[PDB]
Structure formats: structure tokens, C-alpha cells
Image (spheres, coloured by chain):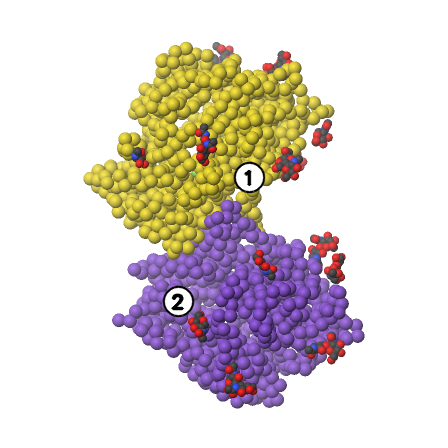
Chain colours: A purple, B yellow
Amino acid sequence: TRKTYTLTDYLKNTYRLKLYSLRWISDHEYLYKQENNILVFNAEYGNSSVFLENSTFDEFGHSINDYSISPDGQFILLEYNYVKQWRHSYTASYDIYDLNKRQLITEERIPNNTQWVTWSPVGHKLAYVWNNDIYVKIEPNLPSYRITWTGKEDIIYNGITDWVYEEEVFSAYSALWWSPNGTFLAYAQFNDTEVPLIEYSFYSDESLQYPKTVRVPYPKAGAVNPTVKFFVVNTDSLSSVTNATSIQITAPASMLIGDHYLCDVTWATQERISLQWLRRIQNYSVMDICDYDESSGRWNCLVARQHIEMSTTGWVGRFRPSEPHFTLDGNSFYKIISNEEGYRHICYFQIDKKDCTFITKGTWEVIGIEALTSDYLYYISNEYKGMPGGRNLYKIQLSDYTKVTCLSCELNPERCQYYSVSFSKEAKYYQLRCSGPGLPLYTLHSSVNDKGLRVLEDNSALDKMLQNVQMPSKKLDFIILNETKFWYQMILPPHFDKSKKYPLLLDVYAGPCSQKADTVFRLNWATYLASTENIIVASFDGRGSGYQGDKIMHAINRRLGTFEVEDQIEAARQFSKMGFVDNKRIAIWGWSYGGYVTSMVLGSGSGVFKCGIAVAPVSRWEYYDSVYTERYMGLPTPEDNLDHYRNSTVMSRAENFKQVEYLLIHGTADDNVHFQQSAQISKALVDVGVDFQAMWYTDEDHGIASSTAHQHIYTHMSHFIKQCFSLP
Amino acid sequence: TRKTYTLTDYLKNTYRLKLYSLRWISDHEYLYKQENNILVFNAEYGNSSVFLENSTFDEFGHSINDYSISPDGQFILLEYNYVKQWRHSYTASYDIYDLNKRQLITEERIPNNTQWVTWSPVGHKLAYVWNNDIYVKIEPNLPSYRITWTGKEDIIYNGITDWVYEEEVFSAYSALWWSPNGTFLAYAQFNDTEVPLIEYSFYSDESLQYPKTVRVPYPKAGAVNPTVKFFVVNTDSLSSVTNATSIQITAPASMLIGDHYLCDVTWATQERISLQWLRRIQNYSVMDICDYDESSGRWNCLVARQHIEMSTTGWVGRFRPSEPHFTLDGNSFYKIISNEEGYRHICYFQIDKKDCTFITKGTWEVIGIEALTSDYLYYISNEYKGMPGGRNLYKIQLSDYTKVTCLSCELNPERCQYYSVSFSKEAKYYQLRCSGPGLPLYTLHSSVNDKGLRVLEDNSALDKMLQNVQMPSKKLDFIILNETKFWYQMILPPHFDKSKKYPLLLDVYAGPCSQKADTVFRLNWATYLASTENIIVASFDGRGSGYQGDKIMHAINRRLGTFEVEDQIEAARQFSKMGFVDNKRIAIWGWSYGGYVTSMVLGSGSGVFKCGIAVAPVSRWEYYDSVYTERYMGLPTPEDNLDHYRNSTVMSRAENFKQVEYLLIHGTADDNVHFQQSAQISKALVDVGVDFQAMWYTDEDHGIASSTAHQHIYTHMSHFIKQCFSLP
Ligand SMILES: CN(C)C(=O)[C@@H]([C@H]1CC[C@H](c2cccc3ncnn32)CC1)[C@H](N)C(=O)N1CC[C@H](F)C1
Ligand SMILES: CN(C)C(=O)[C@@H]([C@H]1CC[C@H](c2cccc3ncnn32)CC1)[C@H](N)C(=O)N1CC[C@H](F)C1
Ligand SMILES: *[C@@H]1O[C@H](CO)[C@@H](O[C@@H]2O[C@H](CO)[C@@H](O)[C@H](O)[C@H]2NC(C)=O)[C@H](O)[C@H]1NC(C)=O
Ligand SMILES: *[C@@H]1O[C@H](CO)[C@@H](O[C@@H]2O[C@H](CO)[C@@H](O)[C@H](O)[C@H]2NC(C)=O)[C@H](O)[C@H]1NC(C)=O
Ligand SMILES: *[C@@H]1O[C@H](CO)[C@@H](O[C@@H]2O[C@H](CO)[C@@H](O)[C@H](O)[C@H]2NC(C)=O)[C@H](O)[C@H]1NC(C)=O
Ligand SMILES: *[C@@H]1O[C@H](CO)[C@@H](O[C@@H]2O[C@H](CO)[C@@H](O)[C@H](O)[C@H]2NC(C)=O)[C@H](O)[C@H]1NC(C)=O
Ligand SMILES: *[C@@H]1O[C@H](CO)[C@@H](O[C@@H]2O[C@H](CO)[C@@H](O)[C@H](O)[C@H]2NC(C)=O)[C@H](O)[C@H]1NC(C)=O
Ligand SMILES: *[C@@H]1O[C@H](CO)[C@@H](O[C@H]2O[C@H](CO)[C@@H](O)[C@H](O)[C@H]2NC(C)=O)[C@H](O)[C@H]1NC(C)=O
Ligand SMILES: *[C@@H]1O[C@H](CO)[C@@H](O[C@H]2O[C@H](CO)[C@@H](O)[C@H](O)[C@H]2NC(C)=O)[C@H](O)[C@H]1NC(C)=O
Ligand SMILES: *[C@H]1O[C@H](CO)[C@@H](O[C@@H]2O[C@H](CO)[C@@H](O)[C@H](O)[C@H]2NC(C)=O)[C@H](O)[C@H]1NC(C)=O
Ligand SMILES: *[C@H]1O[C@H](CO)[C@@H](O[C@@H]2O[C@H](CO)[C@@H](O)[C@H](O)[C@H]2NC(C)=O)[C@H](O)[C@H]1NC(C)=O
Ligand SMILES: *[C@@H]1O[C@H](CO)[C@@H](O)[C@H](O)[C@H]1NC(C)=O
Ligand SMILES: *[C@@H]1O[C@H](CO)[C@@H](O)[C@H](O)[C@H]1NC(C)=O
Ligand SMILES: *[C@@H]1O[C@H](CO)[C@@H](O)[C@H](O)[C@H]1NC(C)=O
Ligand SMILES: *[C@@H]1O[C@H](CO)[C@@H](O)[C@H](O)[C@H]1NC(C)=O
Ligand SMILES: *[C@@H]1O[C@H](CO)[C@@H](O)[C@H](O)[C@H]1NC(C)=O
Ligand SMILES: *[C@@H]1O[C@H](CO)[C@@H](O)[C@H](O)[C@H]1NC(C)=O
Ligand code: NA
């Protein structure tokens, strides 16, 4: 009898998914790491050579965390002493290796504790942030030019984001943008002077006698936000003037009237930069397009080139206003915008005309624009077979919009329905990344004729191994409610028999624009639960979910904690009605927004669920950050949406928890969803006399991803579920 | 057939013990609160009169927390707006009611947020502390004199103790000492300027958007300690035009050489005061005896009247050097000190003589000196029947030490073997409080011929109720380990049948000088476990325990976490050999020091225990405070006792928890044994891959005593124990 996929298999990663991560260095070559040495491949023929022998730095004295070759291939940036900070930020030491003369640079070295470093887009200039100020090096071995002098720990951030801009606005730590050929360096400056601090203890190693108090400028809903300023400096003048002037580009008067955010920066040409602002009440965005005035050294943004977006049935964009993709001459651009029917499609704009032209349409959505050439625009969408959970690459002829070719749909329709892509520098070649429903498949293609060049990685090794395992199957389908279809997926135990009653675990997330029913292949906790414990693990995308139009996505606008919670309960009822579910054993679990929904469901009094597990849950929206929360909830004030803020807390449903088995889990150093959120849930339960299970994870954050903690939480949750389902 | 003592009975206090808390106001009368009314009783005949009507303050407008009548009976201090701080500290608002003119005082009232207040010992002067400074009021309606002006929150403490002196040294917030007739007011001043701060989050009500960070000057082992100065001020010569002058009494030179503490202050006469200082290495104490010099208005402490105490086998005193008990003329005093055999007995000192004479002796110990007259010294000891866990009142004839009379031993030997006493002002009368093995019994007696005047409270009402309940019994016995007897107690289930095998729960504390095997009657969690769940709850006093001599108590000197832990395993090992114990179901639990020992035991790899519960445990001695920790462990430096500090942590034994079920509980706002201690335990268990159960209690301190948390924890622990013992 074949063995099953066990918890240890999952926690020990015995069945490794292979991938093929390459880095395009030009329009025909990419770097690939093999046997620890860096190889360089010729896309056209597939041949290669050793770019950097794995022995080059065997005596460097440190373990290199990552590397980075300058655009002109003359230098390599070595990163070490990596110290993670938030989701994207981290600190590290850096050294530069001169590839030509094959030597390490020992003078004018990048400072220790550098917060961020980036090569210019061309050549080998370097811009970095250290002690919250920006510095530029024209040559790797020469002295740096100081660009800002205002940097101040936890107060003024130049070139880097503060906590909330990192996590919610830019999804990146850097706040600097080189112009195309590297002449100009644009950057933002954040001022968190009056932003309140979240404070929590960090215990560290046992040797630390007194716990440390971590203090981070973090604006909770309705609190004082950081303010921001934008500047551009001409780096080509640095070696000619003692102190190059950073020219500020101010936000439009429509933004200065109140609190606002800088939500996008995209260079259009060597002398044209576009930037976008968003009002704190995120239903109005303004994009400015600014040209360099070579006679005044200033930047001017013609109001005739200003573009505005306004919210209709909800907020603006999926998670932020959409980014612009400029044609080469910088005189027009494309943005994904929801059309009159509520579906997000590509709209083509002339920089000085306010009305754009939709070039795609249909009851489906464009996921992203991937590349743009003089003749074609390439994008990913879920048009194929009307499956919102599928993803394919398409190419549209710019001179004839009726000519749309799907590049990935038919390659291997049964094995591949979820694609991501990576084009070479000028889109001459592209690597396709198939992630499901079958095993991941990586292929390389020629753009000139859209012909497959060769398979890069097919996971044949893993496929061989999995043949000796009773793997679970995955079903993706929909149910119709109120004449609209909602998708769901089920991870089904091996040899699934529909005449039997299986216990069911509802795996939920359900945040705004979320998607938990898709065609991606995953090896995770649910795999073990289905394969070894014979538990059906399901997920449902109800109101509030994404990629299916505004009608569904905006249903929870200003109403978090309502429909997305109820649809999850209704989903469970619908699943039991399918007849292969044991009504006495229906559980529910989620992490993050999933923890919030799980708790709301467990405290709803529905009686449908026997037990549930919430990991790092939000419990009351006033505890979460301003940018994310206010986008969907507005402000927590009586003149706006306070009533719903107070009506959507987990705490107010404490008494109903007497009807279920609850397990609450949270990392104590969670900088994102503060441990505070679960501390208030537990106290509310204690106050009404409800018994429950709990687990805190010392010094773990929102990912509870350290090796030991990861294994410990899934082991702990496994016992809770098996116990709840009376499983040996 | 009748009901058992249930968990709800314990949690809802269904069965309550009646008390008789009286307040002696002279040598002939005492105050007693009845029907919310304050009555005055004549000890001789038992007749009384109403002293204060319960309705007198029906329109006071504030809920009165407590009251304090001035010594002369003329005034009553009304305490309200009570806000708890640490174990003894709290702030409150006060009002003074004139009992002669039956009127509330409205002029010059005590400020709000007063930290401590106290009447002079005679008459009606007042001394209080506010904003860390001392104030004196000669009359309740007159303006107060400012005594100190250096008071500074968390830095300078005048008249009140800082965290460590409150908890570990004086067991009181107050640091003011009135002379016998109220003329002088002595006080200590603490300086915490360089004491590190423990920091932890306080979440508060749900409405608080950002958690608050509590910061408390708290010296952990080896850290910088607060410094102290001592002053005496004449309150009969205060001026409303000039600032009060405080006379300092510097510590002796042998103390000023290094870090030290003030550990006792005791007035001997109207013009003689004694002080005792202890070196930071708590093995050397120096008592000074100072006289007021009318000529220079200074206080002189003759070196000839200096008394030194040194420790050979361990530290000095049980928890601190013993207090002196001066005769009427203040020329000699009595103090409990360990004799040459290591047994604590009463020693008679001459103020200008180095050697003291022991007046009691034997293989037992004097627990405390209770009253002194020219003819007799009254004290409590565990001499009767050689039972270290029993307590009786004795009097010894000062003119003939061979004449010792037990005053409580034979009153009711079956019901009463544990007494406490309260003497009237000049020891003319005494109230005996019997607390076990039977129901509490309170009686009044006259000293002249030791007549038993009357029964004040006999709990006959509770006795009648308990007759309808299947109550457990208590067996107190001993086992012999290496020629030494060690005592234990077992709470046995109703109808105990020695032919059956019962599961056993070892209830442990085991800290230095602890005693968990005694004759006290208690209604607690163990009562329910034995009565309703038929679980035997045992406690054992092994090496390190108190009241049995230094040989036993000092066995763990400089070695906490060794013998006291080993002896608990040995006792369980023995209990498990008895015919009535189920060796497959032996558990262990403890709180505080008890949590540390339980964790050390569960991590010992002994295999004797199936499961255990640790509530707010200490996990590594460097996390606990200096005064308590260094007393038993010395300093955590390589030259002193660092290796043992490092070998005695719970964390180093994590791997051994693989074969036991462990439940770890801790309040997040524990200012005493910081949540840090458990946070480090949980991390070590996660690091070795050991699963366990946990529960944190939001905003609860070391007592986890709020009504809801109390009920929640015992409910959660009860489910854990039953589950471990397979009890329905
Ligand atoms: C799902 N996920 C990772 C998130 O929602 C987090 C981010 C992710 C990037 C988004 C985001 C921001 C800007 C561009 C962009 N393009 C795609 N996403 N995206 C903005 C939301 C969120 N901050 C969070 O941690 N919680 C935690 C509890 C509450 F549920 C929200
Ligand atoms: C039992 N108990 C309440 C204590 O031991 C606490 C105090 C009580 C007064 C004592 C004390 C001090 C001065 C005189 C005196 N006379 C009698 N006791 N006593 C000194 C010890 C201790 N600070 C503590 O909380 N922990 C917590 C974990 C570690 F176990 C010690
Ligand atoms: C991949 O192989 C090709 C062809 O073999 C290599 O092309 C070289 O190109 C240079 C520049 O035009 C010529 O001077 C050489 O003669 C070519 N070499 C050969 C063998 O034909 C190319 O360098 C290889 N690329 C890698 C990364 O190995
Ligand atoms: C960051 O913002 C703060 C405002 O919150 C600025 O601080 C003010 O600066 C002015 C001018 O120096 C002072 O008069 C105010 O008293 C300051 N207010 C506060 C609250 O500090 C600060 O200058 C800004 N810093 C930068 C670099 O822009
Ligand atoms: C480079 O120019 C900037 C911009 O003026 C200088 O920054 C100013 O410095 C002065 C004095 O230190 C401050 O009063 C101003 O508020 C600063 N303005 C800004 C925008 O920071 C900076 O000091 C100059 N650096 C050098 C070396 O001269
Ligand atoms: C990058 O683009 C910049 C901006 O267009 C170029 O700089 C200009 O170059 C022209 C000469 O063709 C000068 O007359 C202008 O004064 C320059 N403008 C500025 C702001 O410096 C620059 O030459 C380009 N760099 C490269 C390597 O092509
Ligand atoms: C409390 O005791 C003090 C000190 O013995 C008494 O004050 C002394 O009284 C005598 C006699 O009147 C004077 O000669 C001294 O000068 C006083 N000494 C001081 C320091 O004041 C005081 O009278 C007593 N108070 C009561 C109520 O008995
Ligand atoms: C207890 O009883 C005595 C009477 O035996 C009370 O009376 C004594 O004190 C009274 C006021 O203090 C006087 O009015 C009596 O004359 C006096 N009698 C004697 C014989 O001394 C006494 O007050 C009572 N005490 C209480 C608290 O009620
Ligand atoms: C309280 O103690 C501090 C020291 O812990 C006293 O200040 C001293 O220490 C300072 C360093 O913190 C030195 O810089 C000072 O010179 C030294 N003396 C003074 C007067 O500050 C402080 O005075 C003490 N306060 C009181 C009221 O005694
Ligand atoms: C301490 O605070 C209390 C409450 O503020 C003060 O008591 C009175 O409070 C009322 C309102 O509740 C005010 O109108 C009065 O002015 C306050 N004083 C009096 C005498 O009524 C109290 O005054 C404060 N303590 C002191 C010493 O002033
Ligand atoms: C009081 O206890 C201390 C600490 O144990 C003793 O001081 C020294 O302790 C070290 C161990 O840390 C020993 O090696 C020394 O022999 C001790 N003496 C000295 C002078 O350092 C101290 O001796 C004890 N005092 C008494 C009277 O027993
Ligand atoms: C590169 O280093 C690896 C060690 O990670 C070694 O196994 C391999 O043989 C080296 N590459 C070559 C081509 O030898
Ligand atoms: C970084 O710090 C290390 C350790 O202090 C030091 O030896 C090294 O020279 C530093 N590097 C730079 C570039 O300053
Ligand atoms: C802008 O947002 C506010 C608050 O959400 C709303 O009242 C207003 O109607 C919105 N305007 C538009 C054009 O959507
Ligand atoms: C005082 O109040 C209590 C209840 O608070 C009441 O029962 C009692 O009768 C009152 N005292 C008197 C003397 O009536
Ligand atoms: C008393 O001392 C304080 C603080 O030193 C001072 O401010 C005040 O003026 C003094 N009053 C007199 C009468 O000296
Ligand atoms: C005596 O018993 C103790 C425990 O009570 C043990 O540690 C010791 O080794 C035994 N022998 C001696 C000589 O103390
Ligand atoms: Na009697």
C-alpha cells in the first residue's frame, strides 16, 4: 500500500518543488544559479558559461546572502550580514567586486548597516540609504555624495519608506527611483514626527536580562499619518557643484487641502516623470505628468496632463490605483481601469487627453500588463474559459485591437492553467511559469515567432516521487447564489467516495479582492490533512473576493465583517448539502484576515461549525493601520463610519463562543496585526466565562515563519483538528 | 448521596469561613465592624456600644473603601477612590470626619491620589505622602507642613518604598515611622535614578487604540540597586514660615563601603530609635541604636550599642533579619536568632552588650514574638508534639526561663493545632485565632490568669452546611530521607479506600523557608479535586523548607533548583509506591516558585509524572529581583555564583519535556515574575520541537485574581487535569 502525504513530509519538505529562477541581464542572456556557481545562459541556443565560480568567495569571510550585478556587467554587489526587518525591509553589509580586474573594492566602501542600495538602471552608479539619508556614488571606488541631511531614526525617512508606506502603499522598502538612463534620482521623504508608536516587548535570546521594547511609528485607523514630500536631483551634476539641489515637486492643490498619500512614481522618459497622489479618503486620485525645464532646472506639471480617478461603487484600484505603462516616446500610457460594467480592463491614454480608450473588454479581468513593445502589449488575464481563478498570457496587436492572441492557453491546457511570465530586457524572449493545476512547468520562448525554445524545468523528479504517494485531488467549481456564481475549491482525500461523509475543514481568508479558489498546485498543510487524515479542505470566494468585477469585490465596501463572513457560513451549508460531508464535523480556520473571518464565524451563533482556529487575527478595525483599513472602512468617526467599526469586532460576539471549540494563536512580536488584537479577544472571552485554547509564539511576527515555530504551530493545530474530529 | 464540594462551590464561594477581625484601640476595648456599623467592645464583659452608624455617610457621595479611626477616637479617616498598585501599594482619596462635632472636614483636605497616610500613634496628627513627598498635619483641619521637596515619580521616594523595597524588604508601601508618642517622624528616602526599568504592555479596555507600556524601576539579579538614606524629623517644632529640618542618620561605615539596604526601623523609646542595615551580600547585618541629643538636636548612635549578625550556613533570618522587641525602658531587647544548633530561638540582648542569652531552646522553632510585659514574653512556636506544621501561643516567665506555659495547646487539641494571636495595647487581653485542623475558632482571653472569657466566632453556621457535603479529609504525616524526617499532607477524597488506586496531584511551592504541609483548614481548588474528582492532592516539604532548623532550610543555599526539586520527585516516587496511588496517573502543579519547581521537575526526565501545570513560574534566576534572588543565590558573576545561575534554568531542560503533558500559564501584566520568564520557556520548547499547552491572561498580574480570570484559570486547569487523568 502506498504511503500518504504526512505532516512530517510537509514540515520537513521531503517532496521539494523545483523552480527555475533566472535573472535577465540583457535582451538575450540570463543568469541562473547551478551547483552554487552563477551561470550565464544564451536564451537563443540554451548554451551557457560560468559567470561566477562558486569558489570565488570561499574566503570572503562571510556567507554572501545575495548578489547583484550592475547593469553594464562591470561590477557585482555582494550582500551579507542580512538582518530582516519588516515584510520587505532589512539591513545588511555590502561589498563591491570589480568583475573585470577580478578584485574586491576596499576603499570608500558602502557603510555597514546600509538600509537599501540600488544600481542605476544603466552603467554602474549606486544610490543607497544609510541612517535615513540618501547617498550616491558615481564610481564604486570613489567617495559618496550626500543628498539629504534630514534623516532621523523613526522620524524622517529619505529614500526609504516608513512602516505603513512599506507594507500598504509601495510594498517595498525603497522610496527612490532612478530616471531611465540614470541622470536623475527621484525620491520621497516621509515625516513621521506626530505618528503614534505601537510598542511591544521583544524578548530575544535567553541571555537578555531585560526585555527590549520595540517602538514603531504606526498609524492605526483614524490616527495621525506620516506626511510626504517628493524630490528630484540631477546626479550628473554632483561632481560639479558642492551641494546638488533636490528640486521638490509639490502635490496638487486638490491634495494639499487635506491629508494625502504619494501612491505611485513612474518615469516616462529621460526628462518626464509621472507621480500620483491619493486623498486620505481614498476615493480620489490625481496623477501629474512632469517635464524637466532645462532653462530653469525645475519640473513643471501641466494641468492638461493631469489625470484623475474617482471611486464609484467602492475604492480605487484593487489594492491601490493602477500603475501606468508608458509607450516609448512618453506621449501615451496604459492603465488597468474598471470599465462601465465593473470589470478591470486596459485603457489607453494620451498624456494630454482625459478620456482613455479601452482596448480590452469582456466579463473577465486583466490581472496585469507585463510588457509593451512598439507593436504589442502583453498582459495576463483570467479570460480563458471564464475561470476567474486561472491565469494566461495574451498579446494584443496595437495597430488592430481585434487581434488578440493567447500565448499560453493551449500549451498544455490540462497541466497548465495558471501562468506568470518574465520577459528579457526588450521582450525578445520570455519565460513562462506554469504553477498549476499540474506540477509547475517552466519554459522559454522566442517573442519574434512565439515559438517554444525548450523546457527549463518540468519537475519530473518530483513527479516520480509523488507516484509512490496517495496524493489528494483538487476540485475547482462554482455554486450559484442569487443568480451569480461563486467559486470554491476542495482538496479531496485519496480515493474520494461521494457516498461517504467526510469531516470538512473550511480554509478561509476572504479579505477584499482575495482569491482562495484557483488552479495553483500546492503542497501544504491541507495536502496532509486530506491525504493522511482524510479531511476535505475547502475554500470559498464569496462577496468581497477579487478578479470577478466590482459588483462582487465592492459588496463589502465600508462593511468589512459582514457579507464575506456570512458567505463563508453559507458556503459550509452548501457543501454539506452536497451529501459527502459529516455535518457533525465541520471546522474552520484562517490566518490574518482569515483569522478575523474565522473568529467572526465562530462567534456568529450559526451552529454550523464545531471548532475553529484563528491565527494572528484582526479583532477590531480601529487596531489596524490607516491606509489599509480606511480604504475599505472610511474613518472611525460618528460623522462617517464609526458605527460599523464598532459593530464588526470579534469581541462583541464573545458570548457566542460558548457554542464552539476555539484555538487562538498569535506571535508576540507581530508588528503588523498587533498581539494586542488577540489580547483583547482572549480578555473578552475570559470576561464572559468562555473556555478556549491558546498559544502565543514568543518573538514571532505575522508570518510565524521561523523554522522551529512553523513546525510547532502546524503540529499544534494538527492535534487540535484531529481531536475536534475525533481522529486517532 | 449528598453533594460533593464542586468547582462552582469553590469559584462562587458557596461555603464561606466566618472571621472576627477586630481592632484593639486600648488595653480594654476593640473595634469590630458589624452590619456595616462600627461597634466598640469592652473585652472584660463583652458588652458593646455603636461607635459609628452605617448610615452616617449615606450621602457621602463616594463608596468608602476603608476607614481608620484616630488613636484618640476623635476623628475617622475615610478612604475612597481606591486604586491598586503592587502587592501592598495603592493610591486613594481621603476625607476626615470629626466625631465630636459630627461633621466632615472641608478645609485643608488630604490631596487626591495620596500614596500613603497614617495617624500618629497617639492623639490625632497625620502624615501622608503625595507625589512622593511627605506632609504632616498637626490638626485635621489645619494646613499641612511640607517635609520633603525632592519627590520625583519613579526616581526619588520619600516616605514610601520603591518596587523592590515594597515587595521584598518591608512588605509595605509605607516608609514612615512615628515615634511612640508622635513627637518625631522617621522616614526613608529611596533613589532609583540608575535602576533599570522592566517594561511590558498593558492593553486596557477595548476602547484603548494603542497598548500602553508600563515602566517600573526594577533591579533584576546583579543589576543596579536603588540607594537609601534615613531621616528623622521633629514634628513638634514645625513652622509655617520655615521649611522643616530633617536630621539624617547615616548607615555605619561597614555598610557604606558597598551596596546595602535598610532592613528594619524600630522605635525603642520616645528618644531612642534602632535601625538595621544589611550588606548587598546578605550575610552581614548591623543594627544601630540611636539616642536623641537635646543639646545638638542630633541623633547619636554609640558604637558600643551596635549589634552585628553574620551568616555562616546561609543567609540572615527567614526572609530578613529579625525585628527587635524592646522592653519598656528600651535598655534591652528580644530577637529571634538561629542558635548553635541552627534552630531559631529567642535571644535576650542588652543594648550595650554583644552577647545575647537564649531564653528558649530545643529542636523546634519560635515563629514570632507577639507581646512583651515586665513579667512575660509571649510567642508562637511549633514546639507542641514536635509538629513543625502546628502553631501555638506560649508565654515564658522572664524571671525564670524554666517556666514556659502553653496557652493554646490544650484549648481544643482535636480542632485546634494552628494559632495566631492579637494582644490588646498592654497585653491585658488577647484574641486567639485557631485556623485548623477543624473550622476556624476565634476566642477572647484575659492575660492575668489566662481565663478563656468567651467565644467570638465558632463557624457553627458553616459547620451545619458542610454536614450535607462529602468533604475530603487531610492526612498530615512524614517520610524519612537519610535519617531526616520530612513532612507531607494529603487531601484525601471522601470515603477514602486504601484498597483502591487514586490518581495523585502533587501541589508544590517549595521555595526557601516555605511550608506546604500544615494543620490549616482550607477550602480551595484541592478541596474540589478531592471531593468531586476523587484525586489525592499531596504537598511535601523537603530540603529548603522552613521552621525546622537551618540544616534543612539552608540545604539549598546558593543552589536553588536542586535539592528542593529533587526532594519533590523523591516524595512522589515514594507516594507512588503506596498501595492507594495510581503510578500511571501522578501529576504536579505550582504557582510562582511552585511553577519553577514544577517546570524543573517536569524537565528532570524522572518519568514519574504524566503531566504538570506551571502558573507564572520563575524560569531563570537572572530574571528575578536582586533582593530576593541574591539572598539565596549570591551574584551572577563568574567570581561568585554565575555557573549555578546558568545551570538552574527551566530552558536548559526543554528536551526532557518530550515525554510529559505541560500546561504553561502567565498573566501578561505580571510586574513581579515578568511574563518574560514564561515567554523564554515557551521559546525553548518550540526550539526543541516539544508540544505543550499554554494560556496567557491579558492584563492580569502575579495573582491572576480578577474575578473573571480567577474563575477562567481554575476552569481551564480543571479540564487539563481531568483530561490527563482520564476523568469524565
Ligand atoms: C493579503 N496581504 C498579504 C495583505 O492584505 C497585506 C497587504 C499586501 C499588499 C497589498 C498591496 C499594496 C500595493 C500594491 C499591491 N499590489 C498587490 N497588492 N498590493 C496591500 C495589502 C496587508 N497589509 C495585511 O497584512 N493585512 C493583515 C490583516 C489584514 F487582513 C490586512
Ligand atoms: C511567597 N511569597 C508571597 C514570596 O516569596 C514574595 C515575598 C513575600 C514576603 C517575604 C518577606 C519579606 C520580609 C519579611 C517577611 N516576613 C515574612 N515574609 N517576609 C519575601 C518574599 C516574593 N517576592 C515572590 O513574589 N516571589 C515570586 C517568585 C519567587 F518565588 C519569589
Ligand atoms: C553560446 O554559444 C555561442 C556559439 O557557440 C557563443 O558565441 C560566440 O559569439 C562570439 C561573439 O560573436 C564569437 O566570437 C564566438 O566565436 C562564439 N563562440 C562560438 C563557440 O561560436 C556564445 O559565446 C555562447 N554563450 C555562452 C554564455 O556560453
Ligand atoms: C517633520 O514634521 C514636523 C511637524 O510635525 C516638523 O517639526 C516642526 O518644525 C517647525 C519648524 O522647525 C517647528 O516650528 C515646530 O515646532 C515643529 N513641530 C514639531 C511637532 O516638531 C519638522 O520640521 C518636519 N521635518 C522635516 C525634515 O520636514
Ligand atoms: C545642502 O543643501 C541643503 C539644502 O539647503 C542644506 O540643508 C539645509 O541646511 C541648513 C543648515 O544646516 C538648514 O537650516 C536647512 O533647513 C536645510 N534644508 C534642507 C532642505 O535640509 C544642507 O545643509 C546642505 N549641505 C551642505 C554640506 O551644505
Ligand atoms: C540621459 O538623459 C539626460 C536628459 O535628457 C541627458 O542629459 C541632457 O543631455 C543633453 C545633451 O544631449 C544636454 O544638452 C542637457 O543639458 C542634458 N540634460 C540634463 C538634465 O543633464 C543625458 O545626456 C542622457 N545620458 C545618457 C548617458 O544618454
Ligand atoms: C513625647 O516625647 C518627647 C521626647 O521625650 C517629649 O518632648 C520633650 O518634652 C520634655 C518635657 O516637656 C522637654 O524638656 C523636651 O525638650 C522635649 N523634647 C523634644 C524633642 O521635644 C514630648 O513632650 C512627648 N509628648 C507626649 C505627648 O508625651
Ligand atoms: C460596658 O459596660 C460598662 C458597664 O458595666 C459600661 O459602663 C462604664 O462606662 C460607661 C461609659 O464609658 C459609663 O457610663 C459607666 O458608668 C461605666 N460603668 C462602670 C461600672 O465602669 C461601658 O461603657 C460599656 N462599654 C461599652 C463599649 O459599651
Ligand atoms: C539620586 O542619585 C543620583 C545618582 O544615582 C544622584 O546624582 C548623582 O549621579 C548623577 C548621575 O546620574 C551625577 O551626574 C551627579 O553628579 C550626582 N549628583 C547629583 C546631585 O546629581 C542624585 O543627586 C540623587 N538624588 C537625590 C535627591 O539624592
Ligand atoms: C482631587 O480631585 C477631586 C475631584 O476633581 C477634587 O474634589 C472636588 O471635585 C469637584 C468635582 O467633582 C470640584 O468641583 C471641586 O473643586 C473639588 N474640590 C472640592 C473641595 O470639592 C479635589 O478638590 C481634589 N483634591 C484637592 C486636594 O483639591
Ligand atoms: C557570607 O556569604 C558570602 C558569600 O557566600 C561569603 O563571602 C565569600 O564567598 C565566596 C564565594 O562566593 C567564598 O569563596 C569566600 O570564602 C567567602 N568569604 C570571603 C571573605 O570572600 C562570606 O564569607 C559569608 N560570611 C560569613 C560570616 O559566613
Ligand atoms: C560548485 O560548488 C558546489 C558546492 O555547492 C560543488 O558541488 C560543485 O562541484 C561546484 N561546481 C563545479 C562545476 O564543480
Ligand atoms: C563593518 O564593521 C566591521 C566590524 O566592526 C568592520 O571590521 C568593517 O571594517 C566595517 N566595514 C565597513 C565598510 O566599514
Ligand atoms: C468620495 O468619498 C467620500 C467618502 O467615502 C464620499 O462621501 C464621496 O461621495 C466620494 N466621491 C466619489 C466621487 O465617489
Ligand atoms: C446598615 O446597613 C445594612 C446593609 O448595608 C443593614 O442591613 C443594617 O440594618 C444597617 N444598620 C442598622 C443599624 O440598621
Ligand atoms: C522651602 O524649600 C523649597 C524647595 O527647596 C523652596 O522652593 C521654598 O521657597 C522654601 N521655603 C522656605 C520658607 O524656605
Ligand atoms: C543524606 O541525604 C541527603 C538528602 O537528604 C543526600 O543528598 C546525601 O547525599 C545523603 N548523605 C549525606 C552524607 O548527606
Ligand atoms: Na468563657
- Would you identify the image quadrant in which residue A518 lies? bottom left
- Image position of B533 with respect to A566: above or below: above
Q: What is the count of numbered marks?
A: 2
Q: What SS does tag 2 mark?
A: loop
Task: Please provide percent x and percent y for residue B226.
Answer: 56, 36
Q: Secondary structure at mark 1?
A: loop
- Amino acid type at circle 2 is Asn
Q: Which mark is residue A13?
A: 2
Q: Pinpoint residue A213: horizontal percent, then vertical percent.
A: 55, 50
Q: Is residue A589 above or below residue B622?
A: below
Quadrant where the C terminus of chain A is found in the figure: bottom left
Question: Residue A355 got which mark?
Answer: none
- Crowd class of label 2 (few under 14; some 14 to 19; many from 20; radius 10 Å): few
Question: What is the three-letter code of the residue carrying label 1?
Answer: Val
Residue nearer the viewer, A519 or B106 = A519
Residue A13 picture quarter: bottom left
Q: Which residue is mark 1?
A: B224
